[PDB]
Image (cartoon, rainbow, N blue to C red; front, side, top):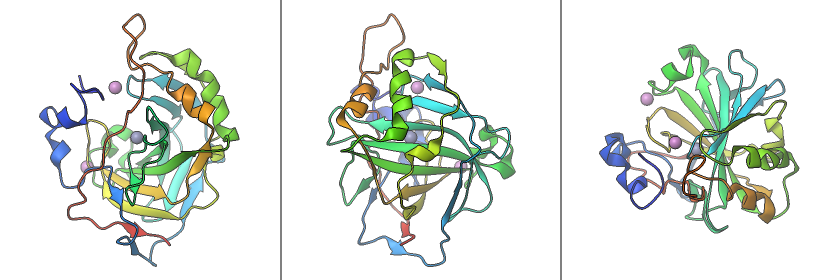
Length: 256
Ligand SMILES: [Hg+2]
Ligand SMILES: [Hg+2]
Ligand SMILES: [Zn+2]
């Protein structure tokens, strides 16, 4: 099935998911000189004090940290959004080398990794219903550069051993996502899509301007994961990123 190799890679996705060549595909290169300052855009409202993480699972293309979204416990509001979006899960995209790994680029610059905090619009009732709407999801994108260690990420780094291969999961309670936010909440926003099949065009992207730094050894542990299931030939989970797509008819707005 789809993956990130030379034979089932992003360049092949269109065959099984024609939307791959759609009008609002993600990710994109953020041209900073062309982005438009929009003064009508409100500050982002991140309310994660009551977040309930549940588990971590290796789904064969990334590792997701899943949260309880049966109530308005960890929500996103404000910015270019309308209403309340509940956090369902967070995951990352990383490279084989520190010079690549992010999906979005800034003036063509690529970061070592990119974090995506996935949220769904509560007037649609469930995640499944949300993906069929134009304003169904909100994804908060955070870049990672290699430098100093990020204290708040080590709990995630330490459990990776436990979910090495596809289909493994581990209890992952009391993880606070607040430890992954940069100091500033300045962002860029545009209408896009999921970056993995089914590539549904139901996402409002919010990409923070300020990256968080992680140590070389923290990113190293990400690179130890496997795309393959247990007892299969080992294939390192590396370069699970989709390259930039054409902006086409869209405008990228800046909150600053
Ligand atoms: Hg997958
Ligand atoms: Hg949609
Ligand atoms: Zn993602």
